[PDB]
Amino acid sequence: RVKPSASLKLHHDLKLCLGDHSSVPVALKGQGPFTLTYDIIETFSSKRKTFEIKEIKTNEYVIKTPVFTTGGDYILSLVSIKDSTGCVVGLSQPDAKIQVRRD
Image (cartoon, rainbow, N blue to C red; front, side, top):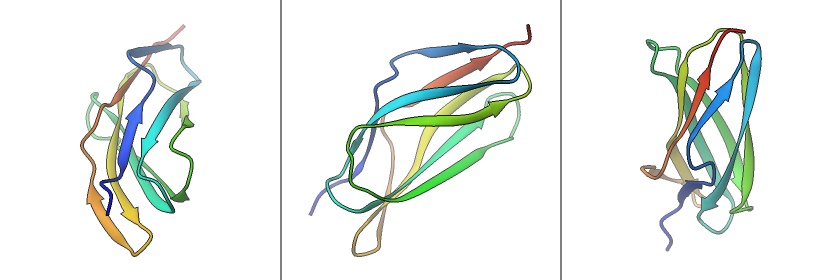
């Protein structure tokens, strides 16, 4: 039994322009086919984005965050992960920040 999760390698906020997307490298936790769910959430209000990649067997995967067509402030956090037996684990490990601006 393992406690799976994610540990982002991007160790600070990202400076983007408008219409920019980002790429946050994450050395993920949990060894085996895990369903990795994470939230790219806005601190701006509630445009919380959610992405789920099943059976991540990587433990070192750089994530590509969707294009931000508006300068704002976002945090990529971890929602939940899933063991290959179908066991969802509450993810609470380091998060990333994506700060988008308008050029």
